[PDB]
Image 1 (cartoon, rainbow, N blue to C red):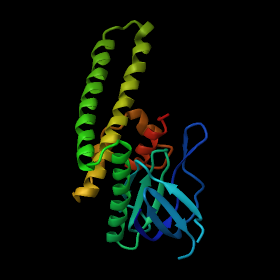
Image 2: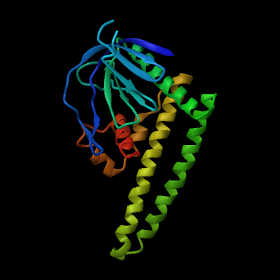
Image 3: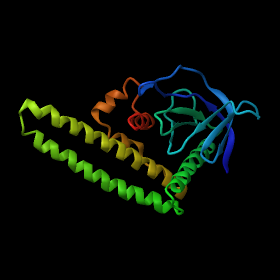
Length: 231
């Protein structure tokens, strides 16, 4: 099934190079493409019948990029693979349709892959589930903390800190999925897209620096950084 199709400009921004090492990618240049969202895959064409290259976007996160320096109508996509790409729509409204279609397709595929029919219920579930799961590990971390900050025995001192660092990550994963869920939800119920600043607000100081050698701190990169940890 095809939901959208039109002219866009491409330029992959970040790829997960060998050994889970996100790379700023070979600084290529913007180049048009007749793109078509069929199901949950983005097929690219060079002329208005052979796909120059395809792109799967299951469980992806599309985010506008108006702060962009040079061009406008920029929008960045990040798939569940630590990858990041950039696009340019005809108009602000085109972008909004593009975003909405991409998200819609993921929200459908996701609801389907979860053997569920009503998506808005499934999505709405996730959020409430994820919030709970976040509150859970949120307390777990706060356990070891107001505990290891007691056992001054450099012996296990570090040993514990490896669980703190662990949960801190489980929490970043959780906030990410939660952010995505809300993105899908809005791209269906037509509400405004979840505030990104709110997600970045949960970036582990480590992950922050981590996403330092990858341009600047953005939701899209954070997403990449989280997928990179997935098996």
